[PDB]
Length: 129
Ligand SMILES: [Cl-]
Ligand SMILES: [Cl-]
Ligand SMILES: [Cl-]
Ligand SMILES: [Cl-]
Ligand SMILES: [Cl-]
Ligand SMILES: [Cl-]
Ligand SMILES: [Cl-]
Ligand code: NA
Image 1: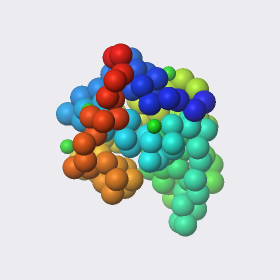
Image 2 (image 1 turned 135 degrees about the vertical axis):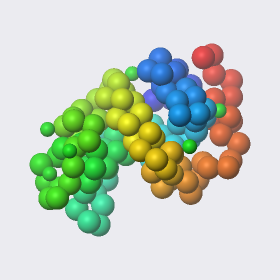
Image 3 (image 1 turned 30 degrees about the vertical axis):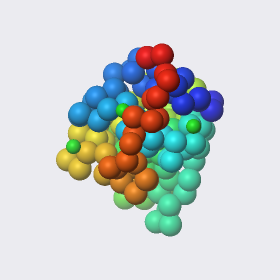
């Protein structure tokens, strides 16, 4: 599924991400935009052989099981394929564990490089939330 901006903002708020660990909804929408372009089916292989999955590009090195990331963990206790669903519940639940892990949203390098410090409220501007 390819979400629209306000459609995703609404779904993220529906699943309790708005202001989770103090990160406003615009931070989450901006991270999704630059990680996946709002596409739930996005996959991208890393140089080290891990893969990032879904709307928030969650990495198999730590967070989900894809059966092909030797030495990796599965701290969200989910198959990485669950992170590609039209329903974002699994991605949200796992993202809540990642952003609690100690470095907040810096875990998402695209958030650190493209969203952090910016006018992230623009991402929810106009949305009926
Ligand atoms: Cl957009
Ligand atoms: Cl915001
Ligand atoms: Cl594996
Ligand atoms: Cl594990
Ligand atoms: Cl699995
Ligand atoms: Cl959803
Ligand atoms: Cl923080
Ligand atoms: Na893994």
